[PDB]
Image (cartoon, coloured by chain):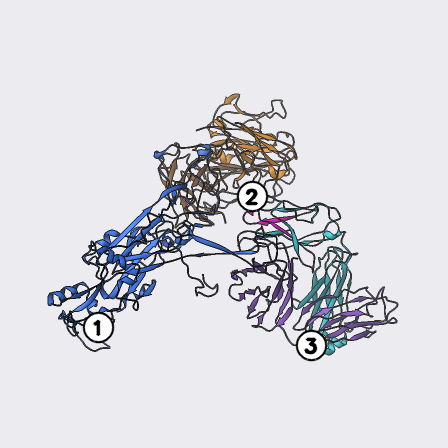
Chain colours: A blue, B orange, C brown, D purple, E cyan
């Protein structure tokens, strides 16, 4: 929602099918003393947080929402037809809606979740592209941003570029690029620090069978059938697409409101969150319910009229986060320092070591020549490497910095952490 | 692969009259689900671009008064025509939209009006410039005659000439509606100054008597 | 809006190749089927085939199987017809347009193009040949109304034109249609007044733009 | 019930700004689309655009893109039209109403408003200029029925009025429509009796409320 | 972005007669699913508010007798009018409800009744108060003439005056149905007392003879 003349948003667009992205800061442990700090040297070493266990609270009453589009390319029912269809007019689009595939997932790690989608690249140049050609396809990884859309079962791609009609799908997805996680490339990471853990459940089934209506891109070669006549003189459009249909939802398949416990993950990180930083990304279809209310512009007249009532739509959203954490130290040697500095050197900035110490070791390869000039050859003066790199990438934010407490007992979640390990006397 | 039959070939008529050409073909343009009829109708005035008249059966195209209304049912069809004015004269076609490849009608040529004519025959024996060229060129002129029907025969000193006969024709004119058709018998000059008298007969239904037009070399 | 440019005319040798063009306005050129129809007097309408520029798929009726060939390009937005290895009966009008197929319709036709005519085979351009005629044994103008005529023959290629006294007299002007003798030929006549001839001047004016030959031939009595 | 107040009239300078209003009765003011239609004699009906007060969404046709602007407020329950940077041809009637769109209907119209007229650009108010006419070489009343006339010109702005002998005679009263010369001008005539003139009194009475100028001009013979 | 053609411009008629204006436009106001016709009909008497008449094709609005019944089919349409009385005279409009933005028809102006008139031409050479003002104001009067057709020309001492011509017109009156049109040629006084004779000719189809009205300075 935005002011009509302005570009400024009046109301933010939100629905369940938007992905969620949570970024969570932690205060530096090493700024942060202890009741008894004697057990380590803070000089020769450091302190770094670790994430043992995680919860996701969700409080709404469970129910399914939905979407549609007023204009949709459609021919007619393909399921049962007494007689052959009618002649194709101009713009037979109709108002029809459908339910999206029910889905649940969870994502955790220190590096942003990596996405992928279909999309258009540049055709190799032999044939000059004429309007109406089939644009070639390309597989593209990208960082995942908030507000992005789950698949509905139409697959990750850019409708905006690849779909000109702009009417071929219901609204919510028409604008953006629905995206989907690739477990492979992610888990293929050498450090695994993208994500160390995850869970997913989803299901779908067919409901209806329809036809696109539009200019035929290609006709099947005849030999795959036999010529018609009369009503069969002409071939109806070849296209079809299913209508995805959500199923019965249960309280059981809910993956939330229940604790988790991590020890070993497919990645070599064990719950280490570098740079005091941690990521969670979660998406649910189950709360999608859309309440609808009506306002009366005139309260007097006693005869019902469709004139008196405007209609609006707002959607509920409820999250909670509770994170266990563990505390850890690091010894320093060369091998250590080396091995880290390889992995991500930016990490070492926010610490001291004590710092001068690895401010680059590498002698240059000797690119050299004039140190002045306005006259002789071109030279470089670009360099800066963008120290808050991902600030380009917007997404939802929460600060915890202030909230830590030192006693599990006082919280609902924690005492379970005790119970799992027992030990009824709090250390 | 089907075949259409387009009849009648030609009809003379008068203003306001109701005339009906016929449509005939092998199979059925029509089976009933959508009750589709595949007949077409096209008007072509001579030399200009054809145009669409009526398809199916009951179609009425935009721009056509009821002077044209479709007719025919089942397989073979007709065209009803209500009241004809001068502009209605044209060369019609009726054809088929069904079962590729396409099939067409023969042709429909409307004939204008009034009644007959009297035949006018003359003869112009070959000028010497034609005999200078080395050939013997004998034509015959028949002008302002209606309808087209005529017969042509050539008797050389009594001996009938079979073959080598050439002809051409010109259609109606606005006033007369009658015709001008040209006849030609042309060979080398060797026979002309040899064979004396020649005979060219014209047989119109007007003047049922066998009107004959002859001539000789060196004489009229 | 709806428009086609059906352009050109041609005469060529036997066994040669030919070219045709029809161009688009007011729609997408490549989005439908297209037609080519051969117009031969005395036979006339015949459906060659059809082509759909989207991929350029083809339809070739048993008749034109082989020799006939069809392609087009939409950036040109202009139809083509490629035919080779000509022949005499090939001479005719190729008169084509585009049916609606899609368009919320099916076959038959909403339109007819400009028209184009092709003639095969040819010769080299020649000059007219004009011999007028008269009656035998001399003509002084006797009879009710004396008649004379002059014809144009021995000319190739088309066209030619004749006018009596600069078209001063329409009486008898019944110029008969041309025909190819191996040289195109036609005939013409004029109906003059028995009294005014030979007195009043009688002249026929030849006009053959192909050979670019124009001849004004006066008609006077002879034996 | 259904009612609109299309009010005001205005004359303004070039490049200036203007204001319009149309008000509601018997329905919800903000629940539908609304219209503005420009009425220019010799051209007349033209559809500017439309606005839906719910959010005040807009439609601007290619013509009025830019300069035209539309807003309204429902607490006022009155339409507005905001236009700036005027021009000469801008002068015309802006005559608007509200179509039913919803209402169990679609476009075209159930209604037409009051009407309002706008004129641009202006000058400062001026007084009439009246010169009557007669025949040359003197007029004593000769002829079957003598005719005379007096015209009103050199006046700005509109309107003016003329009456012959306090409207005592309707014969010949064929006052022709006004036009702007840089000062509005019209013409008028009267058909009187050859006998009664000069005898019977002939007087034309000017009435220009804009300048508030009223002049009673008697008509008598002259050379 | 389509265009509507509204014809004929004007028609004179008599009471009770059946008259039909025409509707013409580029594309189809009509396709068949709901078979929507987008033509509209509006009646406007001069100076008052317009009003709705008929939309679609077969609409009959509340309060309209069959004196107005819609007509037309396919693309371009017509209006049937049954029997006309005096109150039926007005300025009609027909327009479109389809394919935003909106499109309108040109205009329909009905013409009343009876037959012609005779031309009445007088001249009032400039009064001195006009030449006192400094200009030369030469008008011409034509009253009670029907129909509107007239031609105006100005010959200055025989030399034709091209430009600077001014005109205005008044329509029918109840009784006469005829007209009064004002013609004007006005320049500075410099030429008036210099150039002598002036000529103003009026050409109505009534009195096909080239009726001329001239005059001179200082003389009638």
Q: Circle 1 sits on which residue?
A: A377
Q: Residues within 10 Å of mark 3 (few under 14, many from 20)?
A: some
Chain of the residue that carries numbered disc 3 in the rendered image: D
Q: Nearer the viewer, mark 3 or mark 1?
A: 3
Q: Nearer the viewer, residue C200 or D95?
A: D95
The reply to whether the C-beta atoms of the residues labelled 2 and 3 are less than 8 Å apart is no
Q: Quadrant of the C terminus of chain A?
A: bottom left
- Horizontal and vertical percent for residue B176? 63, 35
Residue D149 in sight here: no
Q: Is residue E192 left or right of residue B23?
A: right
Q: Which mark is residue E35?
A: 2
Residue D55 horizontal/vertical position (percent): 51, 61
Rendering coords of residue B41 (x, y %): 53, 35
The image quadrant of residue D174 is bottom right
**Contact, mark 3 vs mark 1 (Cβ under 8 Å):** no
**How far is disc 3 from disc 1 in space, using C-alphas?**
77 Å
Start and end of the magenta stretch? E20-48
Asked whether the residues under marks 1 and 2 belong to the same chain, the reply is no
Residue drawn 58% across and 44% down?
Answer: C167
**Picture disc at residue D126:** 3
Q: Residue furthest front?
A: A425
């Amino acid at each position: 929602i935005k002011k009509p003349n302005n570009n400024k948003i009046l109301v933010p667009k939100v629905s369940g099918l938007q992905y969620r992205v949570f970024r969570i800061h932690l205060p530096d442990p090493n700024k942060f003393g202890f009741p008894d700090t004697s057990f380590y040297n803070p000089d020769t070493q450091r302190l770094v947080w670790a994430c043992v266990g995680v919860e996701v609270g969700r409080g709404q009453p469970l129910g399914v929402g939905i979407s549609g589009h007023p204009l949709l390319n459609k021919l007619d029912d393909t399921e049962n037809a007494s007689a052959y269809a009618a002649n194709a007019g101009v713009d037979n689009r109709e108002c029809i809606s459908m339910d999206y595939k029910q889905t649940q997932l969870c994502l955790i790690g220190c590096k942003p979740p990596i996405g992928e989608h279909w999309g258009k690249g540049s055709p190799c140049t032999n044939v000059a592209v004429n309007p109406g050609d089939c644009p070639p396809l390309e597989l593209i990884n990208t960082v995942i941003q908030d507000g992005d859309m789950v698949d509905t079962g139409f697959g990750a791609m850019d409708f905006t570029t690849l779909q000109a009609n702009k009417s071929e799908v219901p609204l919510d997805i028409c604008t953006s690029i629905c995206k989907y996680p690739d477990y492979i490339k992610m888990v293929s990471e050498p450090y695994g620090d993208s994500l160390f853990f995850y869970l997913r459940r989803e299901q779908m089934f067919v409901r209806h069978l329809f036809n696109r209506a539009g200019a035929v891109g290609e006709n099947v070669p005849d030999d795959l059938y036999i010529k018609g006549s009369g009503s069969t003189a002409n071939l109806a459009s070849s296209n079809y697409f299913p209508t995805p249909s959500g199923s019965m939802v249960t309280s059981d398949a809910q993956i939330f409101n229940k604790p988790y416990w991590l020890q070993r993950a497919q990645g070599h990180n064990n719950g280490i969150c570098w740079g005091n930083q941690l990521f969670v990304t979660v998406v649910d279809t189950t709360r999608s319910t859309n309440m609808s209310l009506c306002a009366a512009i005139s309260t007097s007249e006693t005869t019902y009229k469709n004139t008196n009532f405007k209609e609006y739509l707002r959607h509920g959203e409820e999250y909670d986060l509770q994170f266990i954490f563990q505390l850890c130290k690091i010894t320093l040697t060369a091998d250590v320092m080396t091995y880290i500095h390889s992995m991500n050197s930016t990490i070492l900035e926010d610490w001291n070591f004590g710092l001068q110490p690895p401010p680059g070791g590498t002698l240059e390869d000797t690119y050299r020549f004039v140190t002045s000039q306005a006259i002789a050859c071109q030279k470089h003066t670009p360099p800066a490497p963008k120290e808050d790199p991902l600030k380009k990438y917007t997404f939802w934010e929460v600060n915890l910095k202030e909230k830590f407490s030192a006693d599990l007992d006082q919280f609902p979640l924690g005492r379970k952490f005790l119970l799992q390990a027992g030990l009824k006397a709090k250390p | 692969d089907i075949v259409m039959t387009q009849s009648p070939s030609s009809l003379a008529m008068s203003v306001g009259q109701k005339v009906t050409m016929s449509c005939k073909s092998s199979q059925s343009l029509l089976d009933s689900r959508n009750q589709k009829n595949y007949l077409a109708w096209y008007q072509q005035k001579p030399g200009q671009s054809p145009k669409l008249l009526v398809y199916f059966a009951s179609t009425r195209e935009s721009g056509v008064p009821d002077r044209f209304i479709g007719s025919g049912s089942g397989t073979d069809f007709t065209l009803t025509i209500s009241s004809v004015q001068a502009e209605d004269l044209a060369d019609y076609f009726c054809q088929q939209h069904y079962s590729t490849p396409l099939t067409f009608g023969a042709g429909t040529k409307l004939e204008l009006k009034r009644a007959d004519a009297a035949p006018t025959v003359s003869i112009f024996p070959p000028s010497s410039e034609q005999l200078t060229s080395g050939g013997a060129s004998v034509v015959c002129f028949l002008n302002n005659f209606y309808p087209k029907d005529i017969n042509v025969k050539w008797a050389i000193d009594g001996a009938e000439r079979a073959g080598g006969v050439l002809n051409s024709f010109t259609g109606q004119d606005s006033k007369d509606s009658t015709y001008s058709m040209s006849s030609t018998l042309t060979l080398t000059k060797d026979e002309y100054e040899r064979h004396a008298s020649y005979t060219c007969e014209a047989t119109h239904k007007t003047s049922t008597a066998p009107i004959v037009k002859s001539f000789n070399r060196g004489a009229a | 809006e709806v428009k086609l440019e059906q352009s050109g005319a041609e005469l060529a040798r036997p066994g040669a190749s030919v070219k045709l063009s029809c161009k688009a306005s007011g729609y997408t050129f490549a989005s439908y089927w297209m037609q080519w129809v051969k117009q031969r007097p005395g036979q006339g309408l015949e459906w060659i085939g059809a082509i759909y520029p989207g991929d350029g798929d083809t339809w070739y009726t048993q008749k034109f199987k082989g020799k006939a060939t069809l392609t087009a390009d939409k950036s040109s937005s202009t139809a083509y017809m490629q035919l080779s290895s000509l022949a005499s009966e090939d001479s005719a009008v190729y008169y084509c347009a585009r049916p609606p197929y899609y368009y919320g319709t099916t076959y038959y036709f909403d339109y007819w193009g400009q028209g184009t005519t092709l003639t095969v085979s040819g010769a080299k351009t020649t000059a007219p040949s004009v011999y007028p005629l008269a009656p035998a044994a001399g003509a002084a103008g006797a009879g009710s109304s004396v008649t004379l005529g002059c014809l144009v023959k021995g000319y190739f290629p088309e066209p030619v034109t004749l006018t009596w006294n600069s078209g001063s007299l329409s009486s008898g002007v019944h110029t008969f249609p041309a025909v190819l003798a191996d040289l195109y030929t036609l005939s013409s006549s004029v109906t003059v007044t028995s009294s005014t001839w030979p007195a009043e001047s009688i002249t026929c004016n030849v006009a053959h733009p192909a050979s670019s030959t124009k001849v004004d031939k006066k008609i006077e009595p002879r034996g």
